[PDB]
Length: 345
Ligand SMILES: Nc1ccccc1Nc1ccc(C(=O)c2ccccc2)cc1
Ligand SMILES: CCCCCCCCO[C@@H]1O[C@H](CO)[C@@H](O)[C@H](O)[C@H]1O
Ligand SMILES: CCCCCCCCO[C@@H]1O[C@H](CO)[C@@H](O)[C@H](O)[C@H]1O
Image (cartoon, rainbow, N blue to C red; front, side, top):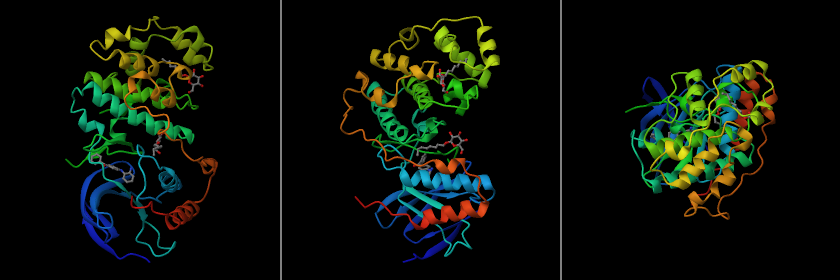
């Protein structure tokens, strides 16, 4: 049953993977692990293999490992990262120290294919459609991404797109704040799912114009540039702000009106402009949802209400728990062992 493993060293780190994975080649890394391209001899497809970095170093790393594995085991949608395989070279819990995750290799992300460049209107429709199709699914399981940015959006040669949990922050050969909802930067501590729609708006704008929509130098500059486009908060939004200091500061600003978006995005498909107007609203309760956005006329050539599925319910109850490092490790180990690969279809 247990496959036979082999060892090699890659960028000062040891990789121990089953023989089925061949021609490991680094493609990059992030805060939580390093990623290699490989050939999967079982399917004949190319895969991405992520080795998590120091998965059980602290209580927080351990819980973060468990969270990532539990999440990735639940995602089963064409526009969301899915797990082909999860393995460890350990034969038992006592020696369990390394965790590797496997997904379909995409080969690029939207940090790249922007090229700092204009994409055509039809390419924008298709890419933003797939993003929203993925988010409808994610949001239906009451998961909010919260950190959407071009690097989270993996794209293959067919322009097929998947949302990653974490992309490559470094590529073996773009500020995150640029894509953040204003409520995130104000530390609201309670979020709507439409925090992610804000980010989509930012990405859609950039693809249509070739320019970063709000290239702030910091969170304060970021908000300054946002208010410039969308205007200062209205009385209706103001009613909903409990924070006295946030309210007092906002009300003390030289008040500004919402710009005419048609003027800002001159030349763009008016349907795209209309959709941008419905994503980029300060008040998160008035932003369009992923489900509503799919049914916007902009996506008429793609929208299929019978092929935009929702997710099985997802149990996030472990988030409220405070466990020992060996308990998170053991729970993660149980998840490695219970893993059922998808069919080769
Ligand atoms: N997050 C995670 C979880 C489990 C396994 C892997 C990952 N992470 C990635 C998945 C796919 C890719 C790419 O296909 C890619 C993107 C940009 C450039 C080259 C290739 C990159 C990272
Ligand atoms: C599979 C697609 C859904 C992915 C949902 C989780 C995306 C990552 O979630 C991010 O994790 C970070 C580190 O833990 C946190 O600091 C961020 O607040 C959070 O947005
Ligand atoms: C310059 C600062 C203005 C930013 C105002 C952001 C308002 C975001 O919108 C708020 O989102 C909350 C969820 O986080 C909801 O609870 C509120 O009902 C909603 O109005």
